[PDB]
Image (cartoon, coloured by chain):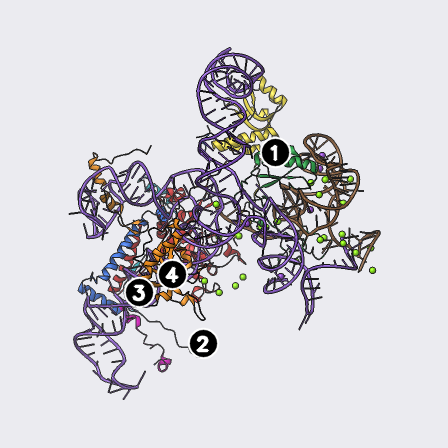
Chain colours: A green, B cyan, C yellow, D orange, E blue, F red, G brown, H purple
RNA sequence: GAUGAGUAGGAGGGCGCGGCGGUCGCUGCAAAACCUUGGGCGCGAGCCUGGGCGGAGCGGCCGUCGGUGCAGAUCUUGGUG
RNA sequence: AAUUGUCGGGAGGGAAGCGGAUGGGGGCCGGCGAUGCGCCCCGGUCGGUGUGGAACGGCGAGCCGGUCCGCCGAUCGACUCGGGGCGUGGACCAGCGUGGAUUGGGGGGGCGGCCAAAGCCCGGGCUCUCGAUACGCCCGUGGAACGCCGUCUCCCCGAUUGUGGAAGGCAGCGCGCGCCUCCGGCGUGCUUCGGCAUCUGCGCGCUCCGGACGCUGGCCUGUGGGCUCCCCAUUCGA
């Protein structure tokens, strides 16, 4: 399958937004939280501090949610759901759900080859 | 005055405006030459720094 | 920097769509979105806006008041973005063509008995 | 028919004569008489089934009206000019410029006998044109073109003979100028205190 | 009763792009041609060393008037009103 | 026709000045009818009166520029925002460059680039202005329809001056950059357009 | 076409947890949980997936509901420097 | 999970961590990167106008259809069928060319303004000296070059960048549609006598013209390429 997308993917930022002071404290997890403190230097955006996520970082709508291979992911749990991508094989690629058995993955992979549907994790748990 | 000016203009088919206008820029003109009086700064005198002098 | 208020953006709120989930109302909105755009008619634009409005902004119209405003205008079609109710204080009901979102059971019976017609906005 | 352009250009896109002047020169007045006092009116100049239908409509790029123009030749470079190669395996060697090919590249020769540089194509951006000129009037390279340097290792004997034929006519001209043979046999290099932006070539 | 069924142009600098300027001001071409032709004549005239628009009497009057005006421009005050500083002012 | 008129006015002024010189008198040039105003200070710490006047002049951003007709009403407004602006008398060259390079028309309260004469005609057509040359002529001569023609022009978004400013905090007379600089506004228009 | 600061505060659109009414699925050919210098998506809350461990359950979607989201409270209980 | 031992990698001149930017060393990734397509004949395989049936349909009794089976005629076509020949070529990176937009820098030319520059040079008249061999004043429609300011215009170099994917539109021209000796010449109207959108329509083309195209090379299981992952170093911030 030849991906239909042609515009290059431009990531405004590739680093993640780490919660402030999650390095200092084990109990403070890395998932982002907006600092609400009155004196918070991060909230006040002093230079040399952690950056906060804002809408300006939004990616181009034409390349948003596109994988590096040039397709968009759709999660499939069986062979029937795979057939939904027959007419979108140049736009959407399939990914087999993490909990599908190896026996049922062989059926999905074989069916995807007939439909020319890209499978992102076709080598999963077959050894 | 505005009513009559518009009436006098309506009969002759000439659309005009009766609005007042603020003072605009003056046009160019020639001024006849005359004797020129030269103005220069005055030398300072401390005695004159008082109404009527010291 | 730019010396504007709220970055030059509007701070006014108006209804751009009905708040209701009524499937029939949404079909009427689609019908009159098309009519307003493709005709430029002021009547269609007004009708479209009133279909968005809340219940209190679509008050009912009594049949008696409908008759008084329709006196001497039999040929014209009465249009109401709202409900038409029956009025026991009105005795003589002339034949009239009325378009409304809803007719009460008594109001519909009296209008139909008098030879009139109750229309919907798709028939209008 | 007309032998020369009616309206020479003062600058690119502006003719020397106005519309009123051009009407006289175009002769439309004469044409009007021959056609009953009217300018003649002309008329405008008057499959296999697919084997596969794509699911997504194909998009064709919009029209671009800009057309590439031939590569320009630097004013410093004239036939017979000595060039200094600035890059590649022959960096620093002094060669003789013969002509510019249709691709815009420069055709140069060592000559091969003096410095071992054969008939080769060198990009203009990687050479410096000096002020030394060697006569190449007797050199004939009309047979050489872009296709002569196209791939399809032993060098065929045909090209070796072709090098010598072009080379032979050029050696006599080079030998005429004293110390020119040694000049073309030595590579150019920068020594201490040598500033390229001040060097005269 | 329905009415019949119904992208930004990249702005280019007309001060540099000739065709863009002619689209806005067609007379600009005539102005361009005349300026180029006028300059060419002057350049040619200077090389050939090619050789008045005022009467001889008029020229004399103009020189006299300008010379008289210049005299008033450089004229100085007599500094007579400063009686207390006559010596200092010279 | 406009090109011929501009040349005649320039030569007409020269002739009159020479005529007055010959007779020994003076020729007072006509007072400037058109001004070009540029905002040189930012939007921080604005006193309320200055803030309102700059809004009425459509100077809401530093280095924005607009034309302004000369009359006692407008001149007195300008006098009250002297330290925040610099202005002067624009010549024909300045008006051409501004309108041609940075000219945008206000159509239905939208900023539209003057790429074609159709844009000018869409708004000013009823006033007889159908091309950018007509628009230039109306501005330079301050014609009868100056108000509509000038308001049709979106305030010019000029760049920071090439070469910088001297001192925005002082008046041009003191060696600064604020206030009336008369014909020297053109020198600044070159470096900011 | 214009435009983008925000404490107290307001509102919108979304993310996540556990049930219920439905609907579409997964699982001893290995579910949940947990581990990982595997990889990717989203501005972000989060999401998807490889490998490992584990050995019996689980998830998506629509609606609807709630004892539904923690770094602090000399917070509680337990554990540990 | 806190916390601890051990093995392995790494760092450490009175904290460490953290933001941003690269680099070194690791680790990881083949949807990390293609190998097809078009046209030929050799063979193989599989189906083909007009009449018969079977089960149905679109439009609204009647017209208008396809699918499947069979029979004739017609004799071609198809083929993720196998070989051969010819043409063509994918991902990423780099270079170059020609241009658009934005922008910085450099060089030249024309014209105008001034005391219709001043001055200087030439010619003429006056004045006649202490810094001693002057100081300067006035004249000429004399001459050769500058100066400042304004304006018109030509050329050269570098930098960043290609968003859009429906339109050969808009604008300005060229060549034909009439002849000549062809850098140009030949007809009306207007003209400042230089010129002029006054005649300047059609057809086919060109261009600074409704947003970048073209060419070439490198590399493609490698010591390659990529990386948002890991450790560390360095400059800035903190
Ligand atoms: K369920
Ligand atoms: K994981
Ligand atoms: K739920
Ligand atoms: K100049
Ligand atoms: K470029
Ligand atoms: K490669
Ligand atoms: K650092
Ligand atoms: Mg990210
Ligand atoms: Mg505070
Ligand atoms: Mg798993
Ligand atoms: Mg802003
Ligand atoms: Mg605000
Ligand atoms: Mg301040
Ligand atoms: Mg702006
Ligand atoms: Mg600079
Ligand atoms: Mg400064
Ligand atoms: Mg201050
Ligand atoms: Mg905000
Ligand atoms: Mg759940
Ligand atoms: Mg870890
Ligand atoms: Mg979920
Ligand atoms: Mg509960
Ligand atoms: Mg709770
Ligand atoms: Mg806690
Ligand atoms: Mg808290
Ligand atoms: Mg505690
Ligand atoms: Mg405790
Ligand atoms: Mg303890
Ligand atoms: Mg642990
Ligand atoms: Mg001059
Ligand atoms: Mg593009």
Comparing labels 2 and 3, the label whose residue is closer to the camera: 3
> Which mark is first along the chain, 4 or 3?
4
Vertical arrangement, residue A53 with respect to residue A119, above or below: below
- Where does label 2 land, which residue? B49
Instruction: Tell us which disc is closer to us: 2 or 4.
Output: 4
Q: Which residue is mark 1?
A: A84
Between marks 1 and 3 in the image, the one whose residue lies nearer the viewer: 3
The residue singled out by tag 3 in the image is D176
Q: Which residue is mark 4?
A: D113
The image quadrant of residue F17 is: bottom left
Q: Residues within 10 Å of mark 1 (few under 14, many from 20)?
A: few
Residue B40: x percent and y percent?
36, 73
Q: Chain of mark 2?
A: B
CA–CA distance in space, label 1 to label 2: 102 Å
Which structural element holds mark 4? helix
What is the distance, in whole Å, between disc 2 and disc 4 at their CAs? Answer: 101 Å
Residue A101 screen position, x and y as percent = 70, 37
Split into quadrants, the picture shows ligand 1 in the one at: top right
User: Do the residues indicated by labels 2 and 3 lie within the same chain of the protein?
Assistant: no
Residue A4 picture location, percent across and down: 53, 40
The residue located at (51%, 56%) in the rendering is: F49
Res. D54 visible in picture: yes
Both on one chain, marks 2 and 4?
A: no
| Disc 1/disc 3 C-alpha distance (Å) | 82 Å
Q: Residues within 10 Å of mark 3 (few under 14, many from 20)?
A: few
Gap in angstroms between the C-alphas marked 3 and 4: 16 Å
Q: Which residues are magenta?
A: E69-89
The answer to whether any part of residue F88 appears in the image is: no
């Amino acid at each position: 399958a030849v991906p239909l997308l042609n515009k290059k993917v431009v990531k405004k930022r590739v680093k993640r937004f780490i919660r402030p002071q999650s390095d200092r404290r084990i109990t403070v997890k890395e998932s982002w939280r907006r600092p609400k403190g009155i004196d918070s230097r991060v909230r006040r955006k002093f230079k040399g501090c952690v950056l906060m996520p804002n809408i300006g970082y939004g990616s181009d709508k034409k390349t948003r949610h596109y994988l590096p291979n040039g397709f968009k992911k759709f999660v499939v749990h069986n062979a029937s759901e795979l057939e939904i991508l027959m007419m979108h094989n140049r736009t959407y690629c399939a990914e087999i759900a993490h909990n599908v058995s190896t026996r049922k993955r062989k059926e999905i992979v074989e069916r995807a080859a007939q439909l020319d549907v890209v499978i992102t994790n076709k080598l999963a748990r077959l050894h | 005055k505005n009513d009559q000016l518009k009436a006098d203009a309506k009969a002759r088919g000439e659309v005009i405006s009766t609005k007042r206008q603020p003072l605009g820029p003056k046009p160019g003109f020639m001024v006849e030459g005359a004797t020129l009086e030269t103005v220069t700064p005055i030398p300072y005198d401390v005695v004159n720094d008082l109404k009527g002098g010291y | 920097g730019i010396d504007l208020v709220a970055g030059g953006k509007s701070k006014k709120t108006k209804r751009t769509a009905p708040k209701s989930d009524d499937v029939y109302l949404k079909l009427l909105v689609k019908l009159y979105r098309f009519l307003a755009r493709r005709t430029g008619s002021k009547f269609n634009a007004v009708i479209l806006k009133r279909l968005f409005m809340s219940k209190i902004n679509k008050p009912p119209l009594s049949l008696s008041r409908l008759i008084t405003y329709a006196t001497g205008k039999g040929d014209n079609i009465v249009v109401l973005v709202g409900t038409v109710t029956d009025d026991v204080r009105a005795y003589e009901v002339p034949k009239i063509k009325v378009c409304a979102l809803k007719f009460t059971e008594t109001a519909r019976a009296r209008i139909e008995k008098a030879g009139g017609e109750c229309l919907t906005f798709d028939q209008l | 028919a007309k032998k020369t352009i009616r309206n020479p250009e003062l600058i690119r896109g502006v003719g020397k004569f106005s519309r009123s002047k051009m009407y006289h020169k175009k002769g439309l007045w004469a044409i009007k008489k021959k056609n009953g006092g009217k300018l003649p009116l002309h008329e405008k100049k008057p499959v296999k089934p697919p084997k596969f239908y794509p699911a997504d409509d194909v998009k064709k790029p919009l029209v671009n009206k800009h057309k590439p123009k031939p590569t320009k030749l630097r004013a410093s470079i004239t036939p017979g000019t000595v060039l200094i190669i600035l890059a590649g395996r022959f960096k620093g060697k002094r060669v003789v410029f013969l002509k510019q090919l249709t691709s815009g590249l420069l055709l140069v020769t060592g000559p091969f006998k003096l410095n071992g540089v054969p008939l080769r194509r060198v990009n203009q951006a990687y050479v410096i044109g000096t002020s030394t000129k060697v006569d190449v009037s007797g050199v004939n390279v009309e047979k050489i073109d872009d296709k002569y340097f196209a791939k399809q290792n032993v060098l065929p004997q045909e090209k070796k003979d072709e090098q010598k034929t072009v080379d032979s006519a050029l050696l006599k001209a080079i030998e005429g100028i004293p110390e020119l043979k040694a000049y073309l046999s030595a590579r150019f290099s920068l020594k201490s205190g040598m500033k390229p932006h001040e060097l005269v070539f | 009763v329905v009415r019949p069924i119904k992208r930004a142009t990249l702005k280019k600098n007309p001060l540099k792009n000739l065709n863009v300027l002619l689209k806005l001001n067609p007379y600009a071409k005539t102005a361009r041609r005349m300026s180029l032709l006028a300059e060419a004549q002057r350049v040619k005239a200077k090389k050939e060393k090619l050789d008045h628009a005022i009467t001889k009497e008029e020229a004399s009057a103009i020189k006299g008037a300008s010379h008289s005006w210049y005299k008033t421009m450089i004229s100085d005050s007599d500094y007579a009103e400063f009686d207390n500083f006559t010596k200092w002012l010279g | 026709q406009y090109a011929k008129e501009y040349s005649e006015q320039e030569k007409e002024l020269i002739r009159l000045k020479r005529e007055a010189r010959l007779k020994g008198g003076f020729y007072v040039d006509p007072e400037a009818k058109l001004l070009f105003i540029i905002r040189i200070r930012g939007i921080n710490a604005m006193p309320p009166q200055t803030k309102k006047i700059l809004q009425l002049l459509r100077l809401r951003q530093i280095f924005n520029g607009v034309f302004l007709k000369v009359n006692k009403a407008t001149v007195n407004m300008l006098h009250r925002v002297e330290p925040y602006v610099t202005y002067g008398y624009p010549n024909l060259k300045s008006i051409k460059e501004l309108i041609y390079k940075r000219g945008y028309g206000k159509v239905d309260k939208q900023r539209i680039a003057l790429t074609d004469n159709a844009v000018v005609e869409q708004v000013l057509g009823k006033h007889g202005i159908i091309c950018i040359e007509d628009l230039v002529h109306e501005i330079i001569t301050v014609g009868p329809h100056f108000k509509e023609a000038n308001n049709f022009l979106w305030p010019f978004q000029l760049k920071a001056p090439l070469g910088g400013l001297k001192k925005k905090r002082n008046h041009y007379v003191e060696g600064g950059d604020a206030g009336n600089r008369e014909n020297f506004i053109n020198e600044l228009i070159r470096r900011m357009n």
